Length: 161
Length: 217
Image 1 (cartoon, each protein chain N blue to C red):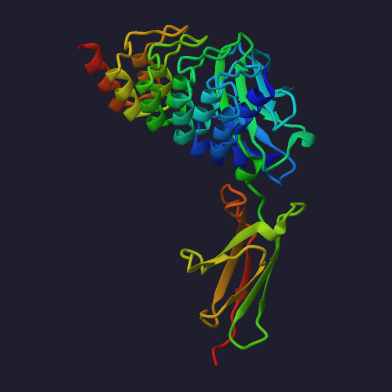
Image 2 (cartoon, chains in turn blue, red):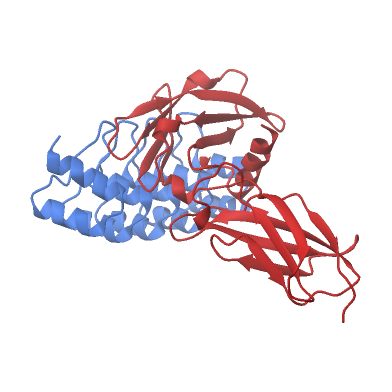
């Protein structure tokens, strides 16, 4: 770790936009990691700050970085429902078929909270509808467990294509 | 604590799937989540990790409790030494296998669910034709200067909710100008922490107090 890198992780988690910029302007490692392996891009997407996520991606943040649990910034944004951040990561080449230690893709996490608009966007970027997690649950199996018939009809139409 | 059960159920109705945290008297924090847990998994199957602004990452003891029917509620009660406010607090629920379950970043001052105010009294005003309400903040709760209140004016059984008055920060009294005479009114007050310095939801209603107005001159 670095004293500038450790400060950048705290600045990104704290939602301090000007601190994040002035830190990597002083030479902070944009791909720094904590003990969990999370980058500032993880924390910026977790707290839901699109302006901080985009500036990290411009300075060279690893969009496909995954922490020790296997969760990427695309995983976290799909969970919390930050569509604008989900769209921003994909434009910078985010892996839509990345799986964590549960075998869950961003399609799994978004469908578990009923984020309908994010599920469609992920499918448009080539999301595997037939991907199963460690429990053998596909993105359709989750929709039946929660019971979102609106979401359940969307994925069946996608698997038939 | 029976009231703690009703506080957890109220937050559970707002968002059942996600991890829920709240503070009562700003010197505590309880994070819980209700899941459809099988008969095999227990509190040792997960790991509740947290980190303050500069403190190292620490583990929180997890307790298992049954809620409703067929569901299990796991909850962590942070030590009082690690209940600082106005600073980022990171949270991670991770199964002992290493699988990710939850990941949150919260501020304790933004999830305050106080207790109901106490000591509500109702008198007539020094001036003619008004009713003065006075109450006390929730007992043993700091920073009463930033607590907002709302009083409820009720009527006879079968109806009520005649008026709703919001009281500004710190002030714990209220004057009522347009009240009918020779009628039984019933009052009640609830408290919440004020924005933008704080955040949360309304607390429970205080124990009510009734009053019968005199004749209108």
